Length: 67
Length: 67
Image (tube, rainbow over all chains, first blue to last red; front, side, top):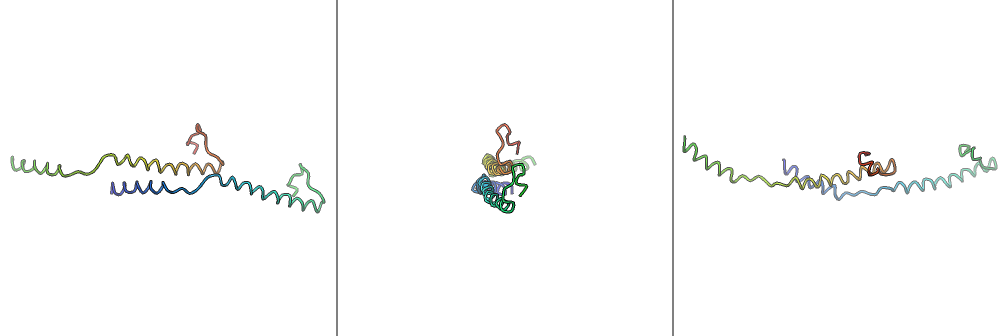
């Protein structure tokens, strides 16, 4: 109640917490790439639409907000 | 009252105190390990959270107090 209730658990605690290694850190950073690479085709491909109707692309100061 | 009240008890005293051996000393030292091992996953796992929002970990002088 004081020893068995504790000492047995102290082991179970560390035995549990020791061999529980879920994963790494930084996988999201790899995801940031495709998130931007996905934009690349989506950006140029979307701009091409505007390059069709107005037959041209927006100006720098005009920015992508024109899209 | 003087002998039976005493001599019988002197035996009962030693007979009792002799065969009453509860436990060891130092079990707490073993507990100190899991207490720190429990922190290990809890430390890195907690730091990983900060490694997510700010996308990185705190500096040495910044210490864990940043967490």
